[PDB]
Image (tube, grey):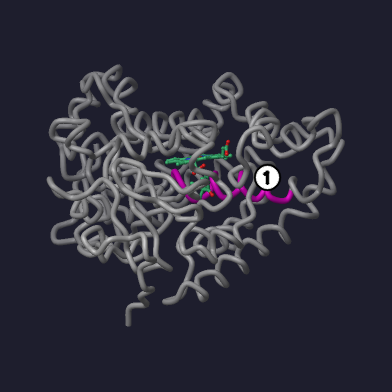
Amino acid sequence: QKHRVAPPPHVPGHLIREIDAYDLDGLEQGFHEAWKRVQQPDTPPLVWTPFTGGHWIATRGTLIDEIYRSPERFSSRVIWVPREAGEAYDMVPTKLDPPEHTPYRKAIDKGLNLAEIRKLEDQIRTIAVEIIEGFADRGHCEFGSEFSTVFPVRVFLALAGLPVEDATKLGLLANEMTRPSGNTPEEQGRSLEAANKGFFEYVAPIIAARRGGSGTDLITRILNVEIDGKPMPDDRALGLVSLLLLGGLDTVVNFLGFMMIYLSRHPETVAEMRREPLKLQRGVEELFRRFAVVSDARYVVSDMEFHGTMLKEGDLILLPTALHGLDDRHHDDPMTVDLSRRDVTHSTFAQGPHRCAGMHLARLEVTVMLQEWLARIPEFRLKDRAVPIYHSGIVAAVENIPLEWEPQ
Ligand code: HEM
Ligand SMILES: CC1(C)[C@H]2CC(=O)[C@]1(C)C[C@H]2O
């Protein structure tokens, strides 16, 4: 049973579209495919759905890019739908606009900048190799449970100086953050609230212990960056460390599954990567263009007209980042991975002040994964008649990816 809200007076009927971000029409055929259905050749750049509490959806790449770049007009004070979940959401600095956002992003960048990330390459590689060598000779694996949900999680927990045995409870919190349970805005609000509380509970003692700490881990490094010449307050720290865990554990995991499904169905593309190692390295960004997973929102700051549509202060606009990288108006044949594509522009990492702090880590993880995978499992296919199971929400997910190959 679908929960509908009535449209507010300023939304005209001709812009209404019944789109459910948490269970997209056509989702069974794929998350990206399902979002692509929304983007028909004549659909308005902004449409409004009565589902998920009622909100706008930007349907074209340049709107998504522009909105992300314009925090003075589109605020991060709510970035989740439904509104109830967005209001309960308590992560730092994603809830902040500049200038409040700025010193916290600086602190994060101390830990996640490209030069710091580069130092991590061999640890990441070691982790990838160990996992791959566990099944490489077997000739088959369930990629989701045996790799994609394992590799990035071990990478991040090691980097964060946390026990790997916490992976399960943290993954469960992550699920209810990005894909909250419930068939009602209030239910989803409550699911998110409880998940966000679980993160704060887990994170509090770690913060207490590592303040002024000597540890070399990501959390200690970032925690002890001063904010305006003072220790980071408790309220902000809780939201900050929770966000690190959330990004580190429930992004790359999902990205990898979508990517691998595609690769397993395009052996020519895999062959190219194999034969030209530089095509692989330089081609990773094209993968990020093609396999966006995040759909989040911004809060309309003032009554305005935007791309010919009237918006009211407080309106939420969902930004399905897949609709930038896959916009046929930005990229010819957007659904094909072309490793040589010169223009790979996308909003997979969003834009503006909040542009993904973890993007260097994400790029390295994927680059290393592909290098060590192809070295040991050069050819592979999706099992005959296998059907991956897809989930849509603030972050997309996919499971059931049985791969098969002839051991080399
Ligand atoms: C496939 C990989 C990833 C994707 C697609 C992705 C996507 C995004 C997006 C779209 C945003 C902007 C959210 C918004 O403000 O509306 C973001 C921000 C952020 N991400 Fe990533 N992310 C990925 C990996 C990571 C990783 C591994 C981390 C490690 C901690 C991370 C940490 C962060 C942080 C801390 C922010 C907030 C930055 C700020 O508000 O200034 N991300 N990410
Ligand atoms: C939307 C995000 C992917 C982004 C901000 C969030 O809350 C995430 C779920 C983790 C971080 O990387």
Residue furthest bottom as drawn? 1
Callout 1: SS? helix
- Position of residue 265 in the picture relative to residue 259 (left or right): left
* x then y, percent, for residue 148: 41, 48
* x then y, percent, for residue 304: 42, 45
- Position of residue 404 in the picture relative to residue 296 (left or right): left
Q: Residue at x 67, y 51 (%)?
A: 163
- Position of residue 16 in the picture relative to residue 178 (left or right): left
Q: How many marks?
A: 1
Magenta segment's dominant SS is helix
Q: Is residue 250 magenta?
A: yes
In the image, which residues are magenta? Answer: 238-252
* Vertical order, 376 against 315 (above or below): above
Q: Residue at x 19, y 25 (%)?
A: 272
* Vertical order, 313 against 24 (above or below): above
* x then y, percent, for residue 263: 23, 40
Residue topped by disc 1: 240
Q: Can residue 125 be seen by looking at this rendering?
A: no
Image quadrant where residue 97 sits: top right
- On the rendered image, what quadrant is the C terminus found in? top left
Q: Is residue 278 magenta?
A: no
Q: Residue at x 54, y 44 (%)?
A: 75
Between residue 40 and residue 375, name the one nearer to us.
40
Between residue 298 and residue 116, name the one nearer to us.
298
- On the rendered image, what quadrant is the N terminus found in? bottom left
Q: Can residue 17 be seen by looking at this rendering?
A: yes
* x then y, percent, for residue 218: 68, 35
Between residue 60 and residue 242, name the one nearer to us.
60
- Position of residue 94 in the picture relative to residue 152 (left or right): right
Amino acid residing under circle 1: Leu
